[PDB]
Image (cartoon, rainbow over all chains, first blue to last red; front, top):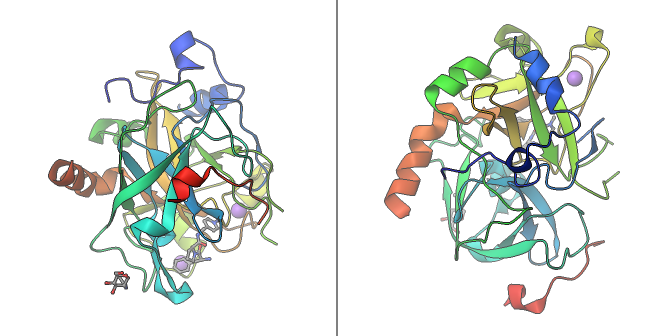
Length: 28
Length: 251
Length: 12
Ligand SMILES: C[n+]1ccc(CNC(=O)[C@@H]2CCCN2C(=O)[C@H](N)Cc2ccccc2)cc1
Ligand SMILES: *[C@@H]1O[C@H](CO)[C@@H](O)[C@H](O)[C@H]1NC(C)=O
Ligand code: NA
Ligand code: NA
């Protein structure tokens, strides 16, 4: 789907979940 | 999930529960990849050493769930299976090589705040993100310990492990269709999938386009969260040609 | 065992 992987309650409203930053920080 | 935490509402809207009809019980996790297709581990459906061989009518899928046991009225949706497809070279005899299966739903599921598909990786996203040290996220309603069960969906973030370390942690033969993840004994932090998390997704959020991709499927492990052991995951990208062939051929 | 019953429609 064109909209795959974008969560209605997070990405769709530009809200971050409590630990996604942990993932981003590992992508060095 | 061992040493994880409660998921936030709508944190994993592609999460699917494979549910046995009789007796009514959790069978496995799975993931929603479109309005009619669900991805899971082959061993969730077929594993002769444990006398497991499910047919379509044995099972339901429950989508949009948070609570493990409650019927989540007005939130979750329950779908019947039209057809199961297991990888033709799934190796249940030896090491769960190619541990992957698709399930086509009888009718499309409506997307909502709580129900939404995850992306499957392209070659470039896989190459970019499937690197030792990079963390993904595993979710499930499985056991909280090796030797009990959660009230709601559990989540844990775990780092991908270097292939030689994966290999050296086990006597089981590892293949290119698998990768492993988890913390080393010296890293302090811990966490792992466990019994009942089988079939659930290992996901990563691409920093390039800010979308979640399913890189892995919970496949196997010796015990749960043991020091010096790691969780093993089906390598979704390596098997994507099969996925696409099934979807293209069968809708 | 400890699962809330689901609506009968889904079990038909
Ligand atoms: C850490 N961890 C991750 C996933 C699971 C769920 N998977 C399982 O329980 C799978 C199903 C068959 C046996 N199994 C296992 O994980 C076995 N313990 C190890 C095994 C691997 C490959 C072939 C035979 C046996 C269990 C534990
Ligand atoms: C599993 O079930 C199918 C059909 O019900 C059967 O044909 C098959 O021989 C069984 N065992 C397998 C696939 O190992
Ligand atoms: Na080894
Ligand atoms: Na471990």
